Image (cartoon, coloured by chain):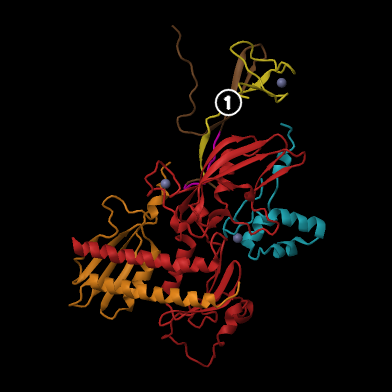
């Protein structure tokens, strides 16, 4: 009876806006971002994507506690490159790759008879 | 294409086997996991057992009802109940099923999924016919009736995803693999006498050349070229399963993007 | 029909006020069941 | 009791295969290894689910009321 | 007048009234048995 209702593993709350930026203090040009109602699904994806970027100096994430559908993500870019920008570019690249995959698989799927 | 290439090895009524190449491991795995977990569909969700005299407890039966795959191809025309303003359900957010059974026979009367009958108006949406993979034509065996036992109830089917409850999964366990030759050395083989003999080499080992032992371990290399196989429970055509998994993942990422827009907004 | 009690043994029907407490009139049993309600109980498919 | 639907781990529907499984056993005399493999239960997460089921609902069905 | 001597069910639990049996005692006292049904799903702390 202390079980949290499972629908809040994907449902933004009240003021639980999907994101919550926080400027890091330990290092310059770095930021820490919190996602609500998320998990490795999105995290590890975006994280590796960032890692692809050349101007990103640091990128890692963590799910603090499995009872909770959050994960913090910490970016750190070189100077003259806002973190939120690196995030935007990572999302865009991911979306383009997904779109390509979608069409390509749809194609090769039509390649069948069943 | 410029990103991933898909090469379908084989496609069936319920499975696609395909090579996923020129991708990153994380993207593959995320795709894997979303297909398992986050692609929405339709399932029984509330049962009004108006009468029951079987030997099964109601909640037992209602449980089995939950698990019955339903035709959910165009689920998108349906609305999450938490979004429909109607008092708990309507035809924009639900499908009403019903069930009556009676042990008219002297022998045992089986009760199959196919006995379910849609009541609510589908509005011409290819939704909710219980999936019948059975060759004999009657779907899941719901319950058995002896003689006088009568079972009569109505159900509500609703859009949901596997995160809330596994019954919504079109999942049907997904296979996954890469570097069958362990060239990446991502794993190390426990063995008593020889790793080579004691480990049955995977069937995918052929699609890549055996490592030439006279080569230094390449550290530059990274894992692409994943061999995946997706089995579909049947509530959705397999190709539709993978396509919608891709699309759902894309949607949620786009949502992140939009949230960034709101932040930079104010 | 609408119902008030069931004989346990005969498995038929019955009705009674605060009168007797026994006697499936046919079998004259001494144990009766309480004739399941009609409230159309609600259930959660999970 | 009655067959479970949906092999617990795997998720694959199995609630329909029960009848055919029994049929194979009786009428085809088949060996349940091959019987399962005939129904398509490849991985043992489902083979377990069927092979080891116990159908008590029979013995429930024998109390008259 | 007359005071209540009811029998509430256990404060912790909940469930469905399963089958209610009414009969007379050995000695002729009307007396009643009630059975409550409940499903228990494995939880974080249950033992196996
Ligand atoms: Zn509605
Ligand atoms: Zn009687
Ligand atoms: Zn399985």
Q: Quadrant of the C terminus of chain A?
A: bottom right
- Mark 1 surroundings within 10 Å by alpha-carbon count, few (fewer than 14), some (14 through 19), many (20 or more): few
Chain (orange): A
> Residue A31 placed where, x, y %?
23, 67
Q: Which residue is drawn at the image coordinates 39% and 56% (left, top)?
A: A66
> Residue D47 placed where, x, y %?
66, 60
Please name the residue that numbered disc 1 is placed on: E34
- Which one is in front, A88 or B69? B69
Q: Is mark 1 within 8 Å of ligand 2?
A: no
Q: Looking at the image, which residue sits at the far top? A: E1
Residue D54 relative to residue B218: left or right:
right
Vertical relation: C31 (above or below) D47? above
Chain (brown): E
Residue E28 relative to residue A17: left or right:
right
Task: Give the drawing colour for chain C.
Answer: yellow
Task: Give the drawing colour for chain D.
Answer: cyan
Q: Is residue D56 visible?
A: no
**What stretch of residues is rendered in magenta?**
E37-44
Q: Chain of mark 1?
A: E
**Helix, strand or loop for the magenta stretch, by majority:** loop
**Secondary structure of the residue carrying numbered label 1:** strand
Residue E43 painted magenta: yes
Residue B152, quarter of the rendered image: top right
Q: Is residue D24 visible?
A: yes
Vertical relation: B143 (above or below) B191? above
Q: Which residue is drawn at the image coordinates 63% and 77% (left, top)?
A: B198
Chain (red): B
Q: Quadrant of the N terminus of chain A?
A: top left
Vertical relation: D55 (above or below) A60? above
Residue D17 painted magenta: no
């Amino acid at each position: 009876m202390n079980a949290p209702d499972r629908f809040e593993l994907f449902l933004l709350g009240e003021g639980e806006s999907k994101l919550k930026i926080d400027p890091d203090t330990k290092a310059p040009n770095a930021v820490v971002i919190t996602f609500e109602k998320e998990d490795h699904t999105l995290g590890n994806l975006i994280r590796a994507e960032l890692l692809n970027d050349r101007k990103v100096l640091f990128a890692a994430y963590k799910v603090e506690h499995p009872f909770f559908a959050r994960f913090k993500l910490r970016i750190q870019t070189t100077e003259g490159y806002d973190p939120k920008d690196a995030l935007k570019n990572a999302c865009n690249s991911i979306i383009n790759k997904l779109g390509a995959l979608k069409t390509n698989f749809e194609t090769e799927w039509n390649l069948q008879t069943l | 294409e410029e990103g991933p290439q898909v090469k379908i090895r084989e496609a069936s009524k319920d499975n696609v086997d395909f090579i996923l190449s020129n991708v990153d491991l994380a993207m593959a795995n995320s795709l894997r996991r979303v297909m398992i977990a986050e692609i929405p569909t339709l399932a029984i969700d509330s049962v009004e057992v108006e009468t029951n005299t079987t030997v099964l407890a109601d909640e037992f039966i209602a449980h089995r009802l939950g698990l019955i795959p339903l035709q959910s191809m165009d689920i998108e025309q349906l609305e999450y109940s938490r979004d429909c303003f109607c008092e708990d359900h309507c035809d924009k957010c639900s499908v009403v099923l019903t069930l009556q059974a009676f042990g008219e026979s002297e022998s045992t009367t089986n009760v199959y999924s196919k006995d379910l009958v849609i009541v609510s108006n589908l509005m011409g949406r290819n939704i909710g016919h219980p999936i019948i993979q059975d060759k004999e034509g009657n779907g899941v065996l719901i319950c058995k009736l002896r003689k006088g036992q009568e079972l009569k109830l109505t159900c509500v089917a609703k859009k949901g995803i596997a995160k809330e409850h596994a019954k919504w999964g079109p999942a049907a366990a997904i296979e996954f693999e890469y570097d069958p030759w362990n060239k990446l050395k991502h794993t190390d083989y426990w063995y008593e006498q020889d790793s080579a003999k004691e480990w049955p080499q995977s069937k995918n080992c052929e699609y890549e050349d055996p490592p030439n032992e006279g080569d230094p371990f390449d550290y530059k290399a990274q894992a692409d070229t994943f061999y995946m196989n997706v089995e579909s429970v049947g509530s959705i055509p397999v190709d539709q399963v993978v396509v919608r998994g891709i699309d759902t993942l894309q949607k949620k990422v786009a949502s992140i993007l939009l949230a960034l827009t709101q932040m930079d907004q104010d | 029909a609408t119902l008030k009690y069931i004989c346990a043994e005969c498995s038929s029907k019955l009705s009674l006020s605060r009168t007797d407490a026994v006697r499936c009139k046919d079998c004259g049993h001494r144990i009766l069941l309480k004739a399941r309600t009609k409230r159309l109980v609600q259930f959660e498919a999970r | 009791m009655i067959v479970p639907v949906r092999c617990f781990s795997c998720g694959k529907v199995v609630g329909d295969k029960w009848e055919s499984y029994l049929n194979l056993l009786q009428e085809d005399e088949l060996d349940e290894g091959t019987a399962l493999s005939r129904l398509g239960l490849k991985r043992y997460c489902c083979r377990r689910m069927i092979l080891t089921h116990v159908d008590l609902i029979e013995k429930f069905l024998r109390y008259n009321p | 007048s007359k005071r209540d001597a009811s029998t509430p069910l256990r404060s912790t639990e909940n469930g469905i009234v399963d089958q209610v049996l009414v009969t007379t005692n050995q000695d002729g006292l009307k007396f009643v048995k009630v059975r409550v049904r409940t499903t228990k799903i494995p939880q974080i702390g249950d033992k196996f």
